[PDB]
Image (tube, rainbow, N blue to C red; front, side):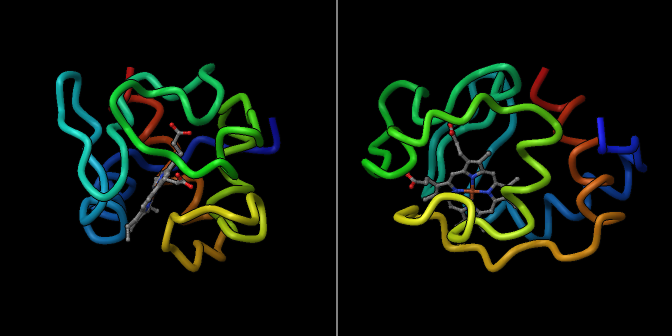
Length: 108
Ligand code: HEM
């Protein structure tokens, strides 16, 4: 870890305002622009069923952990050139820590 637990409540509202437009986090939630994130931690990328991922993200084969995730959020196209994820990134560590604390709980 190089990822410090933040505030899950602060994390939830980041999600709502920066990620809800393309993703759901609930168990049984649907895929939208972006795939559903239920159970993404400890799972490699491009593996949710019934979702058309890029070749890019598939091949990348990232194993998603709090630390991988933090780098990805920093800058998504920079981390996985080729990705269709349209997000510029979360530059502040504090914001990323919060959001990951939230994702950690919500996708379990
Ligand atoms: C900071 C908020 C966000 C979070 C936590 C998030 C998280 C992620 C993660 C973890 C993946 C990879 C999924 C996998 O490997 O199963 C992903 C992929 C994706 N996200 Fe997001 N994302 C966010 C913002 C957005 C937004 C706002 C959009 C839509 C404008 C978006 C669109 C996508 C797309 C299209 C992909 C598929 C990538 C590809 O196939 O190349 N994401 N997202």
